[PDB]
Amino acid sequence: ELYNILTEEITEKNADALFAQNFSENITPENFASQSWIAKYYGLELSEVQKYLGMLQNGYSDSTSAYVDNISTGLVVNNESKLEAYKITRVKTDDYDKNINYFDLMYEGNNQFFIRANFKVSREFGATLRKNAGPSGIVGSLSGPLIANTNFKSNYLSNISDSEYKNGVKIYAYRYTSSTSATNQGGGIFTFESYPLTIFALKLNKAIRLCLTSGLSPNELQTIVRSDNAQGIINDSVLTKVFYTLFYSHRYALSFDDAQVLNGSVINQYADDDSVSHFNRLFNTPPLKGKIFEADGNTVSIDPDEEQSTFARSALMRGLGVNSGELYQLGKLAGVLDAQNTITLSVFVISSLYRLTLLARVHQLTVNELCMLYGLSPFNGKTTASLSSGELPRLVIWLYQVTQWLTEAEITTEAIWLLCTPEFSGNISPEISNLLNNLRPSISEDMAQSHNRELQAEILAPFIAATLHLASPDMARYILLWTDNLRPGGLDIAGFMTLVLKESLNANETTQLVQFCHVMAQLSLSVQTLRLSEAEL
Amino acid sequence: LTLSQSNMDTEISTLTLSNELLLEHITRKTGGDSDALMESLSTYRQAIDTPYHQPYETIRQVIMTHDSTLSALSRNPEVMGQAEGASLLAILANISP
Amino acid sequence: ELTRDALNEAKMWYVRTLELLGDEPEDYGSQQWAAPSLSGAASQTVQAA
Amino acid sequence: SVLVISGFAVLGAKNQPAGQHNIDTLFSLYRFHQWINGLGNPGSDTLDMLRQQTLTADRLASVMGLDISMVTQAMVSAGVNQLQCWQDINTVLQWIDVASALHTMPSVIRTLVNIRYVTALNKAESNLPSWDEWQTLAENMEAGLSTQQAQTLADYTAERLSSVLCNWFLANIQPEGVSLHSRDDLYSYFLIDNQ
Amino acid sequence: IRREAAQMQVEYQETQQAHTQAQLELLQRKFTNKALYSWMRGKLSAIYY
């Protein structure tokens, strides 16, 4: 029944019926306007309730800030007779804590404005941008003088669509210190949701029940649902992702934030007014000398051969714990490479690289070992970022099986790679040269042109056993028959014989010859490593 | 100064406050940026604690952290042989350009 | 005293103390407080008013 | 067998004719032997590819388990364009070794080596990076530090900056009517201890 | 003094590790090594067949 509560879809038609089905007769949607009532009904403290709802707008003083770190209130929309309940969450942006006491986004029914207080007093104005000072980045302005510790309203911000009001950087404090100098003094990324009151209560009911039973933070759960749909609904995919977060955390001894990335979510950036976001702890504690932020969307080269690298690459490198060469390998493995061997600094791309480092770290693999093992996997040829939401857990569990097996059988990553890789030297090694020289005097074109692959294996068996250090000639025969079935370079056992009986008339049939011998050596070494008996083979 | 809760609780190093206080006074007199002051200090000669080439000092500290006594550089003579005698001194001792 | 009767007696005293005290109140004024400047809080006009 | 048949050209010698017997060539032989042993089972095949002139950077990287980017940059920084003999391979490995020691790349090591103090006249000249090139170099070096080590570096920089800024203030700024001559005098004026 | 003896014991264990390294290498540089044996019974098995 709790599963039905969590997963049933909520529409404007059945909202009233669902509320009556989910709450007592003496409970009305207006009860959700009191934070104290919600605390009593759900058995939470007021501080715990504010992790969901933040601060309720109930006519405070004019400065007062409005974020803890969320803002919410009921607003009867004054274009008609509907009553909406909205919620805005903020993620502070580079250099917010120097200058800016607070940078608050306010909602009034279909349009938004800004409220600001400042640390340092300056005599000039401030233009609130949204893009990287682009031609179409201006979304509002603050008329000065911008003195410190003073409230300032901003003129009904305009140039922002409602679709980007979900995950859209509403902010830039392009504040002038002189008549010709301005800098981005900080801000935050704002996310907006609006619902009718009854629907808002039903969604809050889902979130509290799921957080209480799973132990997730309200914002950790919020990030998980944000990685499946924009509407913030709970469904099978979200619940499955929650399970893997709990399961990975127990198994790999990971924090809920690290396990969250492993399940397929982005790095969490939310801060709780007395804590540090997962993103900031990874990349900005301490900062190189300034703050790296994903709220850039800019293009940076991760080419190792690049003269005069970027600050963004250096900060990214230190956060992942890798050097220039390993970062390039992760870019190819993730498939996040772009024109000129560049990446886009977003949460999605950065989380893709961090997910790979987590995948290698929890399995005691280096970055290079992760690349080698992935090549032998049935996932090779597919970039990890271009993997379905069902394939990613399959990759993780596959990596667990192999690494656990290798430790159990005491086989190193290099050893298992040499046993299974299709990559071969392409050179006729001295072992192969000695095999051919010892084989020619005991072989004839008549035997090679016969039809009995069973008889050809018997003739070749003693020579193969000698060159591969096999136990008995009988073992070499079955290795040869296994190789004949595989047809490595298109060569069969008879085709191998005819290539041996050539007066060095090998133009590039050597490629087939060495590939045939490469597979044979792998099969023989695999049998020896497993210590397989001749009867089983 | 804002009498905010964060300004009462948030931990910070005393040197950070002292450095930003001095930085404000220096940049106010010279009119330039904080980064402009750093470049200017890299060639200032009329003091005993200057010239201060901070990026060079950072590089030397990184080397000192990873390998003091230069054992790794000593054990690979092919790469040490391509450095100048004065430049090697700049690794072991603080000598800006 | 660690005995069952002693623990029951101890529980009785604590419950009686808690019923005399009542429910402890929440923090009411901290979140509505607007942060002033140092000179603003020390302003003579604010004190005089 | 391979060394003698090839006239010891496989081993090579720095500025010397190959095949000599002395303590230096014996030392090279010992180090070359250590490399062959570490190669594992493909060692015999790799040695044969080295007797011929068909040993490539890609083959060397995969056999030794190194990253191809590191080997490529090491070759460029060392100045070798072909792996002809052990001397070339040994030189490449040394650039890789110091790159790992400083937690950086061979290209960065080459940049550091190219910083030359040659007195800037009275002889040819000195070769130094620009201010922006210095800042880029510092970021690359600092990116190889752990979080614990980065915090230690930050503490050193803060202490150095405090003494530098105080000395600049003492020599350049004298306030309206106050005479201050010491770090403690700066303490008593600015009401915060910079020491 | 006890610390010195314990440190010497570490050096004793390291020496024993190098001794087994020399034993294994000597086994491989032997004239009658694995390679010689493998080719001889390989040749003789073909002759016997």
Image: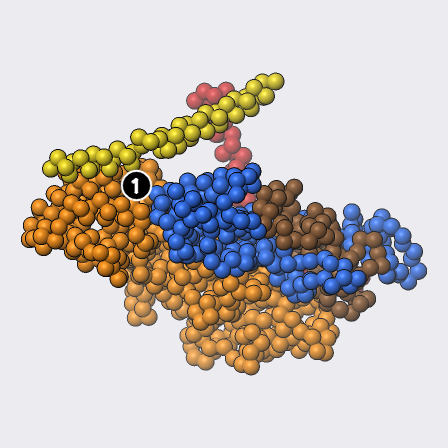
Chain colours: A orange, B brown, C red, D blue, E yellow
Where residue A240 appears, as percent x and y from the top left, is 31, 54
Residue at 67% in and 74% down:
A182
The residue that mark 1 highlights is A405
The chain ID associated with circle 1 is A
Where residue E21 appears, as percent x and y from the top left, is 42, 30
> Which amino acid, by three-letter code, is at mark 1?
Trp
Residue at 65% in and 53% down:
B83
Relative to the observer, which residue lies in front, B81 or C3? Answer: B81
Q: Residue furthest left?
A: A451
Image height of A370 relative to A530, above or below: below
Residue at 25% in and 42% down:
A467
Instruction: Judge from the rendering whether residue A382 lies leftward or rightward of residue D19; answer left or right.
Output: left
| Picture quarter with the C terminus of chain C | bottom right
Image height of D30 relative to B7, above or below: above
Tell me the crowding category of disc 1: few under 14, some 14 to 19, or many 20 or more residues within 10 angstroms, Cα based: few
Is residue D185 visible in the rendered image? The answer is: yes
